[PDB]
Image (cartoon, rainbow, N blue to C red; front, side, top):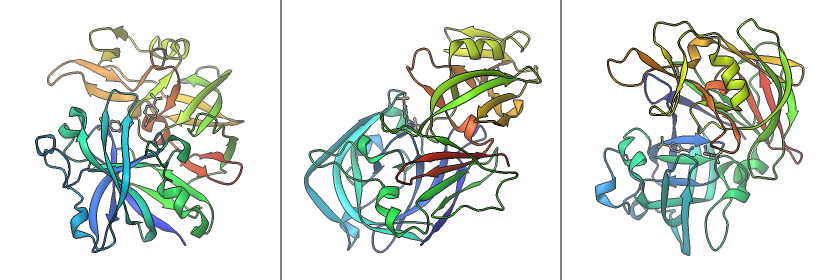
Length: 330
Ligand SMILES: NCc1ccc(C(F)(F)F)cc1
Ligand SMILES: NCc1ccc(C(F)(F)F)cc1
């Protein structure tokens, strides 16, 4: 079997992407943030503290004939940005673009952090990292991808994110019309539970390509690109008036500047991120200082190939027994 669904930016800056997901019988459609950096499927629900819900669509397990409470199971998650949420667990039927999984763990949020309450457009997350990171206690639960793996024509899913435009998540097959040239595959380490790989280097604008191993994770759930300080300093040195602002918490640049592109290596192939992708607009309404989409990972402890990088490519998450990542230009 296969599945195909459209994913759409939540705002004019591509801060996140939402994808409709059907939960329960009869279907309740929620717009989830597909997150290859985490492994929990959790939703706003009828159980969420009422003051912490501000416009989200909620899952109501009492109205699903296939919902089963998972006795004694709880969950609690903290993300790298300080966000968090927690609650109890149901099993239910979940469908993504016509691909169905019965008995999927649906984690009902009882408590959510402020950043989630303020994002009216995201009803929950669908984690697509490896199941070892799932936070359900005392019995760990599998992700949607892991549960669907056996029924899929091929144990893969692909991420085709749009720049200021809708995109596609596909499960079970690789659309050979969605990219140009060849797909370059690279080895994945699962030892930390992430889609972790090693980039072979980078270039700034038309500059010389610098061969250097950059270890990082492919994370649809993270907006920006986070790379080591040396690389990020080399990029922003090419933008007149750019500087790192402690009060703003990152590199900023004059909104009137033109940004150079950024190239990152995948084996012997190159993925080029257009400079326009690196512009995240004014730091505040009316400001002439703009926020940059390439930031330092020094404070994070790991490099993150977030949406800024991934939307420049067609990306294959190959969940074979030896997992690999595929990158192609598009
Ligand atoms: N998108 C989920 C996510 C968020 C943060 C991290 C960090 F910070 F641990 F790298 C990993 C995964
Ligand atoms: N990396 C996972 C993640 C995704 C979205 C959010 C937001 F946007 F709700 F803050 C936080 C964390």
